[PDB]
Image: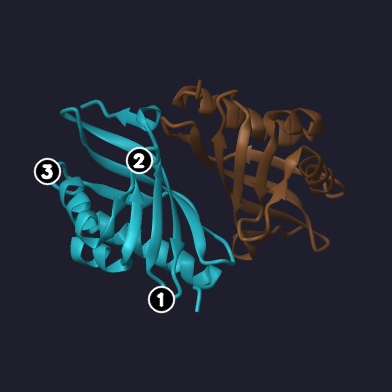
Chain colours: A cyan, B brown
Amino acid sequence: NLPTAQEVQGLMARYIELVDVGDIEAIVQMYADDATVENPFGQPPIHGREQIAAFYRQGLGGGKVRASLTGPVRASHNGSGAMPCRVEMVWNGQPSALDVIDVMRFDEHGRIQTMQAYWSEVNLSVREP
Amino acid sequence: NLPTAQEVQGLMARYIELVDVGDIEAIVQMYADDATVENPFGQPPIHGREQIAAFYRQGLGGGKVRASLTGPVRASHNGSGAMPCRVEMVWNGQPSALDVIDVMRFDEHGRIQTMQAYWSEVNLSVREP
């Protein structure tokens, strides 16, 4: 059955953990095999487990990447939710911080069926040494 | 043309202002006439300016309602964005606070074409004396 509000809060916080540690296997594990990821929202979706793994491979490849929840997960009663996080990584040769909000819909097996990441360069902050 | 990241940031912050002051006319003004609101996401959409006005009428009717941005607006390059806010109002006879994340898609005239508010009772906090 479709994940309750509570469970969605649990699942979306766990996803941020996994991203923080770079556990690509576990991250990919969280997605339905026909899931889609739009990141950043606006770009063409990436489809299916194989492409997604590569996305997270390249994404978490090279620049050291931390992610942390910066507020409560907002969760609906229909297996969806949205959350704000801050992603630390190297951009354009500089340690930078990116503010993001991820929106996720889960299937009846508690897998991510759809993910969208809202952010752009306006949410981008370069850190001084 | 479709609103830039910067403009989206501006528009979504202005919406929160208007809600905070209860300017229903201006709020309704921000929406396309064929816009849809899902609030809370999961419930059936409300369609068009007339129903929307009533929604904001009832919504901002009775319980004193404040709303404030609690972090940066995440804005994409394709006329969409998402933001976190905290809504103060009276629920179930009690001054309460609700954590929300609104997701908005704008049209080429800078009007809100689609709004979704993510929150449920798990995001609800009742305030003591």
Tell me: A94 left or right of B96.
left
- Residue marked by disc 1: A109
Identify the chain of the residue marked 1, using the numbered disc in the image: A
Local secondary structure at mark 3? loop
Label whose residue precedes the other's in the sequence (1 or 3):
3
Q: Amino acid at mark 2?
A: Pro
Residue farthest to the right? B62
Q: Amino acid at mark 1?
A: His
Labels 1 and 2 positioned on one and the same chain: yes
1 and 2 marks in contact (CB < 8 Å): no
User: Which picture quadrant has residue A23?
Assistant: bottom left
Disc 3/disc 2 C-alpha distance (Å)? 19 Å
Q: Amino acid at mark 3?
A: Gly
Q: Residue B33 location in percent, x, y?
A: 72, 34
- Residue marked by disc 3: A62
Q: Residue at x 71, y 57 (%)?
A: B127
Q: Which mark is residue A95?
A: none
- Residue marked by disc 2: A40
Q: Residues within 10 Å of mark 3 (few under 14, many from 20)?
A: few
User: Which picture quadrant has residue B112?
Assistant: top right
Residue farthest to the top? B1
- Residue B4 visible within the image: yes
| Mark toward the viewer: 1 or 3 | 1
| Mark toward the viewer: 3 or 2 | 2
Q: Residue at x 50, y 74 (%)?
A: A2
Label whose residue precedes the other's in the sequence (1 or 2):
2
Disc 1/disc 2 C-alpha distance (Å)? 26 Å
